[PDB]
Every structure is written in structure tokens, then in C-alpha cells.
Amino acid sequence: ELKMDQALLLIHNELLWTNLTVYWKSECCYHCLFQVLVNVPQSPKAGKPSAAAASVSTQHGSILQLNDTLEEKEVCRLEYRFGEFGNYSLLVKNISEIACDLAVNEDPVDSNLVSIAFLIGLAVIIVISFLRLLLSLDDFNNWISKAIPRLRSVDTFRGIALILMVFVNYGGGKYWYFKHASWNGLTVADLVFPWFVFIMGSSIFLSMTSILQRGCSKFRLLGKIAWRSFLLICIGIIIVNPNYCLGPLSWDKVRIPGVLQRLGVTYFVVAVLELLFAKPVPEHCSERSCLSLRDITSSWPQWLLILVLEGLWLGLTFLLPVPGCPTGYLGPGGIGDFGKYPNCTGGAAGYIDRLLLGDDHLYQHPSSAVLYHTEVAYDPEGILGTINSIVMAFLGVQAGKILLYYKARTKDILIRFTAWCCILGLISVALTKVSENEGFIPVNKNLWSLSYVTTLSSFAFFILLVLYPVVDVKGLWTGTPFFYPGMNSILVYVGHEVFENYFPFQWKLKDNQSHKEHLTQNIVATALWVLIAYILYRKKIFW
Amino acid sequence: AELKMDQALLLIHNELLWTNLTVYWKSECCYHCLFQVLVNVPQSPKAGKPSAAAASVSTQHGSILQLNDTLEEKEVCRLEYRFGEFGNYSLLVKNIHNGVSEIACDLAVNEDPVDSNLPVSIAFLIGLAVIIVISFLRLLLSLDDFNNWPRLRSVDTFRGIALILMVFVNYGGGKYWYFKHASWNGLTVADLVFPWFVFIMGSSIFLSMTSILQRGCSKFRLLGKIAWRSFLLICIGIIIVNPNYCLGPLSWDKVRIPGVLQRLGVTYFVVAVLELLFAKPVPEHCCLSLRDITSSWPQWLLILVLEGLWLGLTFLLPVPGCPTGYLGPGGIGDFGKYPNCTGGAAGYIDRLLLGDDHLYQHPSSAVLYHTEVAYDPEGILGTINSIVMAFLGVQAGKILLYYKARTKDILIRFTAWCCILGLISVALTKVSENEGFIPVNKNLWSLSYVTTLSSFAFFILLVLYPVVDVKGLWTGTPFFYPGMNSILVYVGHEVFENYFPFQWKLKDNQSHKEHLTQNIVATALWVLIAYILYRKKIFWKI
Ligand SMILES: *[C@@H]1O[C@H](CO)[C@@H](O[C@@H]2O[C@H](CO)[C@@H](O)[C@H](O)[C@H]2NC(C)=O)[C@H](O)[C@H]1NC(C)=O
Ligand SMILES: *[C@@H]1O[C@H](CO)[C@@H](O)[C@H](O)[C@H]1NC(C)=O
Ligand SMILES: *[C@@H]1O[C@H](CO)[C@@H](O)[C@H](O)[C@H]1NC(C)=O
Ligand SMILES: *[C@@H]1O[C@H](CO)[C@@H](O)[C@H](O)[C@H]1NC(C)=O
Ligand SMILES: *[C@@H]1O[C@H](CO)[C@@H](O)[C@H](O)[C@H]1NC(C)=O
Ligand SMILES: *[C@@H]1O[C@H](CO)[C@@H](O)[C@H](O)[C@H]1NC(C)=O
Ligand SMILES: *[C@@H]1O[C@H](CO)[C@@H](O)[C@H](O)[C@H]1NC(C)=O
Ligand SMILES: *[C@@H]1O[C@H](CO)[C@@H](O)[C@H](O)[C@H]1NC(C)=O
């Protein structure tokens, strides 16, 4: 009967002649219309109330409304939070004063700390497997004997981001907080691509300045950058269009925008801009010497270009009119905002995509469709969000500039990192207030809002601040399993994108509707990808 | 019409007043197939008004029609027509003047298109090939302004040809029966593509191995590299031969273990280690000396022993429910007396070791012989035969290497080997492809199959060695780019087999022209990708 995160609900009417209809609304909505859930017939006789089952989602919160169809007067309003695999028999009865007694026939099953014990057992098994692999490596070394630097902080951060991306791209255990949130708000899966872009820009600066310090030509670097960007865009367009179930995709239903396309475009833009404005690293300098402030001043034209682009983004989002839609719209449409704007997903950001690339070429299953029941096609990797992607890539480039201008000065690097983190956090707090949904520019992924970029950049700066002393300066724990994907980021990304549908990466499940099975499947698949990255790192075949 | 692709309509009219008419059908290329009920036409109720019923007889190749009266099980008539694609082919049966009731079956045709030609492929031959070449030329001319602002090439060309043919036939090849694996015994264009790749793989093994030994390296480093490459090939093959496009992902107990890449990796390891354990330095040649065999008589004896083992297991090992030594297709084969006997002892070993679940469930005989059991072509004894073929490739490499100075001894040895292998194939097969001792078969990897394809590979090398390497008339301009990226391109099209540039919705889903255009476009796309990879000097080769 029930499946996944769906707790059955029993409704019995003990009223007399007020035929009842119940209504449902998720708690996470900002303004959703009360969509109908199930009807309740009139009681056939006194002392014999009728019944009517239902299936209410138990992910996060639940608001129940019971408004009679004969007279629009709410019998009762309930804001209970249902649990997974519950029974939750609900009774409505009169005391004129209609009461609503809610009972729990069966206790809901606990998940995400049963689930804790399963996770601990899986971790123990993984530790045992790692020990066995180490023993096998030692045996191979003994047999051979018998027969006979990017600072690693950038690498570890990119590896962490890529591994989290792989885990959340396999479903992430199908948890509500391990997949992209419906529109506004931040989840674990909403933090892994911005970190990838940030660290990718930092790697762009590090590699480019290392090459320019070494013997190379600017035009050769430009050619390499153009070729790599074109290859990334081509592979993205190829891999964001499977035909596993539907017939082969036609010449028009092809989806142009994608994750790798956005990565290639932002890489090309920021790399060409940096080649246009690239100077040898100055030796501006003992003690703090905070008066230097050379990283920001030495690259003013790039900052001017970034500010111009972001002003363009703000103007287009809050000023450009949209036909049949209020100007400066940020909501998700559908049943959101009381359904007054059925087709306004993204506002101007989606309007530009629909005007340029057409409706059929965009992501036909937006992340907001599950919650807001929207019908318009919206692509999160759209056209107007490329401005913010470029902005965050340049922020990563600035982080690399800070990390490399002060080659061996831990105090200055930490001070600059914490200053940038505090500034970006203050900007984000000012923009989004403190409520996720409320504010000037609420944090969002589908629009790549400025508050989203600032929040993720501040988080990335804090992660770098806590990682650099641990990994490079002091060498506490040198990210043992993480930089192997840190070296083969793009290869591993393409690998799990194209190998997502095969045997070892996903198999038949005894319990199809269960968090534990999906979690222990995705964890094994991600660990397999870590193992593959490690194997390719042993061969020194970095690409 | 409303018919399927490669299927001819068959309208039957009855003029009999006392017998229910049953029509049987059997394709001409069966060796011994039973007759299965195609359609039943009832007797005409009213005199002068024939009963009407329709059937869709397959028009792939050949057709035999037998009409049996269900009243007394008697013979009525017998046709041996060859139907045409998307035809009409109305058939009527009637008596001759009602004299002696000697009823006859006369066939009439109303429309029949023609296939297996170049109706529009001629226009496509230069319609886009010239444009792509011009576009490439324009980029090179523009790049110069922006910029301003030996090797064998014959083994590589042959490997590229074989790889391109495998790519073409793995995408359907226009759905023709030429470019598809034959039903059990028999040869097609798609049956010639894999053993040539194995042959070239062995030859390249010997070439690279002798080159690295002459450069100077430890034998154990090579052994480790070979073992790791074999393990990598086997692993990726196991990963890629199990797609879960079905509604339910493959279970733990239904994964298909054997595959093409498993075969390739196992033969790679076996023959490479065999060559390593008996790798002698090449003598300094100074015409009529049989040195290529007396320098490797140990591994030659080993290969002969392996062939003897294969023959003994195939022709002697008893099988429960099957005769001791069998080669029949299986279902409705050999007059249907052996329902589940596909492969005999060559498939019984597969079932015993790997289990029935872990094998290929839609073998190439299931389309014509209507078999029901699962038999994986890449079995266990097929591994022995593929090892033999790769060893013959190593022998060809030895011939090409030892006599590196003169181009006369090389051609003499290639033609001698080709003649001997062709003679062995003719003796075994008797040149009938159905009877004989060991008929040429791809599913079983028959010894005659290996000898035939080794002779063909030797002739191809004979024609491509002077023209490409020696005289320099040709250099394999579009084909040797996959020559040095065989493994990468194979894995690529096996994983990218279903995506937008390689698979797009068709205007009509059942027409050879559209399928041929799509498959040729995809193969050209893979040629272009291999070219781009070659331009960047990125080489990963087994
Ligand atoms: C169709 O009719 C033919 C001819 O009557 C059948 O062929 C005979 O089958 C019997 C077995 O029942 C054999 O003993 C004869 O040797 C066959 N040939 C003759 C009589 O000439 C045939 O079996 C019938 N059924 C099918 C499916 O073909
Ligand atoms: C159910 O509500 C409808 C109102 O449209 C009406 O038939 C009646 O009030 C209820 N039914 C019964 C049987 O009382
Ligand atoms: C019943 O409840 C609301 C109160 O919020 C009332 O205004 C309306 O008539 C009913 N709601 C719906 C969705 O029918
Ligand atoms: C829920 O509780 C009701 C109360 O009687 C019971 O009839 C029903 O079987 C229960 N369902 C489940 C799934 O436990
Ligand atoms: C919204 O779009 C859907 C299809 O995307 C269409 O059916 C519907 O009529 C549109 N409604 C408005 C108000 O534009
Ligand atoms: C034979 O044909 C007659 C008339 O055509 C029909 O009544 C009878 O059922 C048929 N019998 C069989 C076995 O088909
Ligand atoms: C075959 O011809 C008949 C007339 O002889 C016609 O009625 C029928 O439609 C034709 N079949 C097809 C598939 O067109
Ligand atoms: C052949 O195998 C099938 C597998 O489904 C089985 O049903 C059939 O009985 C087998 N044939 C014989 C003669 O046992």
C-alpha cells in the first residue's frame, strides 16, 4: 500500500449532516494553495462512522485543513507532523464545537539516527575492506620484492566536493535533505557544485600562473583553454541526453544546457579573462604586514568586469519585463504564491531561456515540480545563471591569488581567508535576512541567486581556512581518500554520469522502498568510484 | 504498409469445399527446421466466394510453403518462392477444372520494392563527405593565421578497419542480415570482424613485446603490466556487458559474466605470457629457412595441445540429454529431435560452470531456430579457439618482424600461410557451410572458423603490406586513427551506444535507408572522435 515516505492516514467522520472534505499543504511551502487530499463521506448511521484512507507525505511537516463542502466553515485545523510508516487514525467529532482527536495506532519507524546502526555497520565493513586492501597491497609489494604541488588543500577540497556530488547524483539515499531542495532553501546536495566551481577557478589560477612562470606562450594557453572548453561543452551535451526508457531523443527535444556545459562556459570565460589580465606574482614583501593588500588591487579590471556582469544580472532579474507575468519575479509558480502565476518559474531567468533555447530544449523535470506541482520546463543550468557561475569562479580565482601571493605566510593567508569569509557572510545575511524564503534575494539554486553565491563562497572560504593548516601547514590528516578524485575530477564526473546505469553501480533491491538499502547502495557505489580514482592515481595517469 | 521491416504480406484464398487448409512455413537457410503453423484459412462456406485470411511471411532470405489439409493430414502443394520486402504477394489455391481434384497453388504479385543496393547512398557518398573534408580544410587554413598571429601503418590500418566494422555492426548496420551475426553455422559480414581484431591484437602483442625487449626492460615488469592490463580489460568488460536499461536492474544472480572484452582480455593475458616465457632475441637475417616455426616450437606444441583438447571436449564429452558430440543449432533444429541441445558440450560446460543465469539470454539462434535456452557465444572453449587465433596473429607478427629487410620473403610467407589455412578450411568444411566435419560457426568458435578467418586475415595483410607500408600508394588516411585507440573507441561506443548524436528518433522506424544513414553517421562520428584523440597524442592501447 504505502510506499517510501508516505504515512497512511485514516479519517472517520462522527459528525451528522455536514459532509466533509479535507485539505493538505506541506509545511515547507511559502504560499501554496491547499490541494485536495481525500474526501470523507457522510456517516451512514449514528454510532457507525465511515472511513476514508489517504497517503500524506511525511518528509517535512504537514498542515491539514477540513473545510466542509456544504458550508465553507473549517471543522478543524491540524498542523501535525507525520512520521514514516505510521498509521495515524484521525477522528473528527463534535463536543457545535467540532473536535479533532488524532491518535497514533502504530509508532513511526525511525530513520537517519536502525538507520544509524546500519550506517555504523557499513562503516565498519568499509574499514575492514580497506584493511584487507592494505594487506593485499603489502602482499603485492612483498611478492615484487621476492621476485626482484597544488598545496593538496585545493586537491582535497575538490575531491570532497566531487565525492559529495557523486553521492547526491546517485540519489543520495533518497533522503529529502540529500537531494536538491524545491526552489528556495539550501540542502546538502545544493552545496557541492558551487564548491566545485570555486575550487575549479582556484585551480585555474594556480595552474595558469605556474605555467606562465615556467616556459610557455600565451597563445598556446589560449588554444588549450578554448579546446578544453569546447570538449567539455560537447561531452556535456552528449551526456545530459540519455534515452534509457523513452525513444531516442529527436532533433528538437535535445536538452542543451547542463552541468558540464556550464562548467565549460565559466571555465572559458574566466580563463580567457585571466589570460587577458595576467601579471607576474609581485614580491611585495615579516610580521603581519596587513598594509600590503596587493591581491585585490593588482587585478582591478577583472573586478570591474565581474561587477558589470553582476549588475547586468540584477538588472535583468529585477527589471526586465516578462509577458503574462509580474516583473522581477522570484517565486516558483505552479501552486506557489497562491497559484496566481501558474507559468512564471524563474521569472526573467526562465523567460530568457525559453526565448533563446526554446521550451523543448530545457530541463523538463525541474526540482520544483515535486513540491509546487509546476508544469513549465525550467533548466537550473540556464543562461542567466552563468553570470553568477562566472562570479563564483572568479571568487575562486581570487582565493587562489591569495593562497599563492603569500607563498609561505600562514598568518596572512588565514587572516585574508577569515576576512573574506566574514565579508561574504555579512553580505549574504544582509541580502537574505535570516529566513530562507523571505528576504530581498532568497538563497536559491534554480536561479543561482547572488545570496546563494555569496553564502556558498563564504562556506568555501571557511572550508579552505580549516583545511589549509590541517593538510599543508601542519599535516595533521592529509586527506587520505580524497585527493585521488581531486586529481581526476572531470574524468570521474563523466565516469559516474555515463556508468550510472550498470550492474555494480546499481542492482536489484530486496526492499525497494527503504532508506537503508538505497543508502548502503549509494555509499558502496561512491566508495567504488573512490577506489577507481585511487587506482588511476597509482598509475600516474592524471588528465 | 502496416507490415514490419523485412516482412512480405501473404494473402491466401481458399477454393476448397471439404478441407480446412493449414499453411506451414520454413526459411530456406535452415539445415533441418520443422514446419510451424503460419496461418489457417477455413474452407469457403459458399461456392464461388473464397475465404480470406492474411499472413506476414518473412522476406529476409528464402521461403518454403507447405499446405496441409487438417482433415486427413495430406499434402496439397509446395512452394519455394523468394519473397520481396514490403510486397503484396497474393496467393490462391484452387482445383484444375474439377477433373481429378489436382489442386494447384499459383502465386501472383501486385507490388514489390527492391533493397540491398545504393538508391540514395550514392548521393550521401559525396553529399556530406566532401563538406566535412572542406570544413576540416577551412579550420586548418584558419588555424595557420591564428598560429602566426617508419611506423608499420599496416597492422594499425587493419585494426582500424576491423574496429570500424565492429562499430558499424554493433549499431545494427542498417538492420540488414549481411551486417548481423548468422543464425548458428554460416558466415556474414558481421561474423568477420572480431577474429580479425583478435589476430591483430596478437600481432601487436608480439611487435610491442619485441620492441620493448630490444629497448631493454625486465621480464617481470612486462609480466606485471600485461597482467594488470588483462585485469583492467576483464573488469571494464564485465561492467559494460551488463546494462540495466530494463525496468528492473540486474540482480546479483542474473549478471552476465562472459563478454567480448572478457574474451579479449583472457586471450591477451594467455598469449602475451606465453610469448614472454619463450621470448628469444630476433636473429640477424642474412630466404628458404623455416625459422619462424623452429624458433617457437614450444608454444606451437602448446597451441596444438590446446586444439586437441578443444576437439576432444567438443566431439567426445558426453552431455545429459544430448548426443556425445553435437553442433546443432538447438530448437527445431535437426528436425526438432533435440529441443535443448544448443552447443552440445561447448554450451554444457558453460551451463555447468557459470550457470544458466549468468549467460547471454538472447543468442543469435533465437531469431531463426526459435531456441529457448541461453547460450553465451563467448563461452569457455571459445576462449581456447580465440587463443589459437591470437597465436596465429603472433605468428604473422613474427613473419613480418624477422624478415624486415626484404618485402619478397614476407609476401611469400603470407601467401603460403593463406594457402595452407584455406586448404585446411576447405578440407574441414567441404565448402558447404552446413555439413562437413566442423562447419564454420561463430557461436562455437569452430576450428574451421578460426582457420578460415586466419586465412582471410593473412590475405588482407598480404594486400595491405606492400600498398601501405612498402610502395606507399596508400596510408589508411581515415582508418588508422582508431588503429591506435581501438580499446578506447570500443569502450566508448559500447557505453555511448544510446545517446542523442548516436541515436535519434527516426522519421520511419522500419526502413533500411534511415537505419543505414544513422549507423553510418554514428560510425563517422566515432572516426572523427578517434581522429581528434590522435591529434592530441593521447594513446591508450592494449
Ligand atoms: C504435412 O503433410 C505431410 C505429407 O502428408 C507430412 O509429411 C509426412 O509426415 C509423416 C509423419 O506424420 C512421415 O512419416 C512422412 O514420411 C511424411 N512425408 C510424406 C507422407 O510424404 C507432414 O508430417 C505434415 N505435417 C507437417 C507439419 O509438415
Ligand atoms: C455529501 O455531500 C454532498 C454535497 O454535494 C451531498 O450529497 C451530501 O451533503 C453528502 N452526502 C450524504 C449522503 O449525506
Ligand atoms: C476552507 O478553509 C479556508 C480557510 O483558510 C477557507 O477560506 C476556504 O473556504 C476553504 N479552503 C479551500 C482550499 O477550499
Ligand atoms: C492502521 O490502524 C487501523 C486501525 O484499526 C487498522 O485497521 C489498520 O490495519 C492499520 N494499518 C496498518 C498498515 O497498520
Ligand atoms: C502554462 O503552460 C502550460 C504548458 O506548459 C499550458 O498548458 C497552460 O495553458 C499555460 N497557462 C498559462 C496561464 O499560460
Ligand atoms: C473444417 O471446416 C469446416 C467448414 O469450413 C468447419 O465447420 C470445421 O469446424 C473445420 N474443422 C476444423 C478442425 O478446422
Ligand atoms: C495488397 O493488395 C490488395 C489488393 O490486391 C490490397 O487490398 C491490400 O491492401 C494490399 N496490401 C497492402 C499492405 O497494401
Ligand atoms: C527446455 O528448457 C525449457 C526452459 O524453460 C523447459 O521448459 C523445457 O521443458 C526444456 N525441454 C525439455 C525437453 O525438458
Image (cartoon, coloured by chain):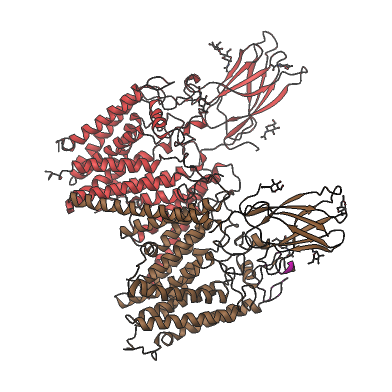
Chain colours: A brown, B red
Residue at 36 percent across and 88 percent down: it is: A288
Q: Most extreme residue toward the bottom, as rendered? A: A291
| Residue B169 place in picture, x, y as percent | 45, 42
Residue at 58 percent across and 77 percent down: it is: A313
User: Is A371 or B296 nearer to us in this picture?
Assistant: A371
User: Is B291 or B215 nearer to us in this picture?
Assistant: B215
> Is residue B483 left or right of B125 when viewed as pictured?
left
- Dominant secondary structure of the residues highlighted in magenta in the image: loop
User: Is A81 or A285 nearer to us in this picture?
Assistant: A81
Residue B416 painted magenta: no
| Residue A409 place in picture, x, y as percent | 33, 82
Q: Is residue B142 visible in this depiction of the protein?
A: no
Residue A337 painted magenta: yes
Q: Image quarter for residue B206? A: top left
| Residue A333 place in picture, x, y as percent | 69, 67
| Residue A476 place in picture, x, y as percent | 34, 70
User: Is A400 or B78 nearer to us in this picture?
Assistant: A400
The quadrant where ligand 3 appears is bottom right
Q: Image quarter for residue A489? A: bottom left
Residue A331 vertical position relative to residue B435 in the rendered view, above or below: below
> Is residue A407 left or right of A56 when viewed as pictured?
left
Residue A318 vertical position relative to residue A292 in the rendered view, above or below: above
Q: Most extreme residue toward the front, as rendered? A: A95
Q: Is residue A3 visible in this depiction of the protein?
A: yes
> Is residue A33 left or right of A3 when viewed as pictured?
right
Residue B335 vertical position relative to residue A177 in the rendered view, above or below: above
Magenta part of the chain: A320-339
